Length: 14
Length: 381
Ligand SMILES: *Cc1ccc(C*)cc1
Image (cartoon, rainbow over all chains, first blue to last red; front, side):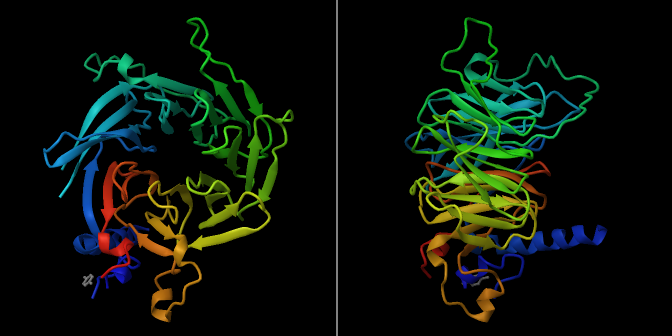
C-alpha cells in the first residue's frame, strides 16, 4: 500500500 | 476558474495527510521572492555530529519591482532542520537560470532576459546588501524579447559555456582566456541551426565536443564543436509534437538522454539512432519545463512543470504487467508523483551528496526540499 499510495497522492490512502 | 483553485487547495490537504507515509523528509520554506532556478552546490559540510550536515543551493529572483538578487541558501539535512539564506548578492535584471561552473563552484553563471550572460564570483562580493544601493530602474521597456532559459558549462573543458541566444541561436563563450581587465567576453562560436526559440541547451557529460539543444521548432539537435559548419548540426529529430523545453543527458549511459516538452511527454533517446524514440513517459497533465536524471541511480529520472506535479520515473519497470486498478494511476514506470507544489514548478535539482533528496521551487515563493520514503524505492514493504 505505500507503492500504490506513491502513484495517487491526491487521493487518501486506505 | 475560481473553483479550480479550490480543487488545488483541497488536494494539497490530502497530500499533507499523505506526507508521513510518502516521505522520509519534507522541508517547506517561503522565499522572499519566487525562484525560476534551483541548483545544489556540490560541497557538503558536515561537521562531525550536530545531527545534521550543511548543504548549499543556488537561487535567484525574477522581479521587476525590486532590486533583484542571486541567493545562496544553506539547508540542514539530518542523519537519523533549518533553511536560512547565506549570501544575497545584487544581480542586475531578472534571474532566469543560475548554474555554477564545475571547475570552481564559486563562479556562478546567470541567464538574463536580455541577450547576455552574467558571471558572478560570490567571494568577490559583500554577503548581504547592507548598502541596499539598488541598480533597479523605475521602468523597463523591453520590445522584441522572447528567450529560453538554457545555460550549461562544459564539465570536460574549463570555461566553455553555452547559452540559448536571442534570435534562434546558441552562443559559445570561452572564459578561460579572460582579456586584460576589459571584462566583456565576446562569443567564440554562434550556432545557427534552430528555426524557433532555443529553450534549453546542455553539454555532453563525457565527450567534450558534443552538446544537445531543444527549441520551439519541435526539434532536438545534437552538435559537435569540431565541425566547420556551425549552421547545421550533426543530427536533427522531429522529437515532439509541441515545444521542447528541457533536455538532460544520462550520467551512466553516454548514448542515452531525455527530452521533456509541451505535449506532456518525456521522450527517451538513443544517440546512435535518433529516428526511434525509445520510450514516451506519459503522466503529466500540462507542459513540462525540467527533466533531470538521478546522479545516484542509472534507472531513475524525474520531470516537472506547469501541472504542479514533479513526476519521478523508473526505466526498470517499463513494459511490466499491470492490473486495471494500477493502470488508472499511471504507467508502471511511474514511481512517484510529488504534489507538494500548489503553483507551477519552475526548476528542480537532485542532491549530489544525499541520495533521493530533491530541492524543487515554484512560483508562489515555495521552495521545497524533500525525499520520498525508503520503502517505495527499494521495492520493499
Ligand atoms: C501501507 C499504507 C500506506 C499508506 C496508508 C495511508 C496506509 C497504509
